[PDB]
Image 1 (cartoon, rainbow, N blue to C red):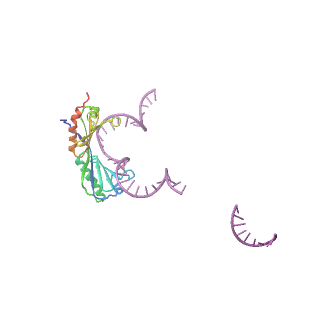
Image 2: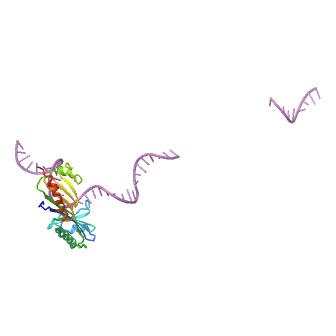
Image 3: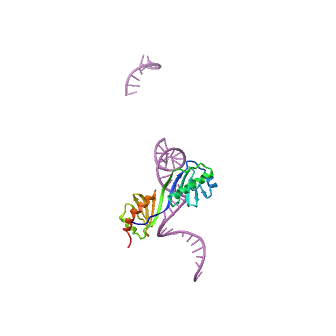
Length: 181
DNA sequence: TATGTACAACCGAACGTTCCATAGCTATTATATACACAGCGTGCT
């Protein structure tokens, strides 16, 4: 009905290697590594070809983020593991689970936020002197939507690409019902 | 009769400080979105 498909903007994927790393060694022998143990307990590393960031912890756990596609995250995570391998550490690609997907879109018309905040009060929270966007907590699929007056919708919380589409197709009608003017 | 001698009667407890045990908050990364606020820098007068 809508005819517009939301576009994914970020994918937070987590990977494990099953081995203990020495963060200082990784920071000193990796191209772009930023290890500051005083603030955080991981070495932050970036690569350019998929443009993703990785938080590599001392327990062999990795948190890749920034990929725009489900497969691109796999390529980024694989390259990060390979870089760790080329250092010499025992690193093997292992369980890869996408823990969060963020998508954005626009319905192309203003939305009366005061309406959703009133009609849908059990899901929507509208406190406009803190954040200019209404927060809709959909119950099935369990996804959080940020609805803005300019007609822009942000989808976050989906674990697969299907739920983020399902949420938008279920939110378009109630959004159109509250079109200003 | 007189004098001796004898006998009978008339400290607690309130508050403060240190020591285990469990759970929860804090910080960091990425991204779309948008508002308000606090800066910095450049032209104008």
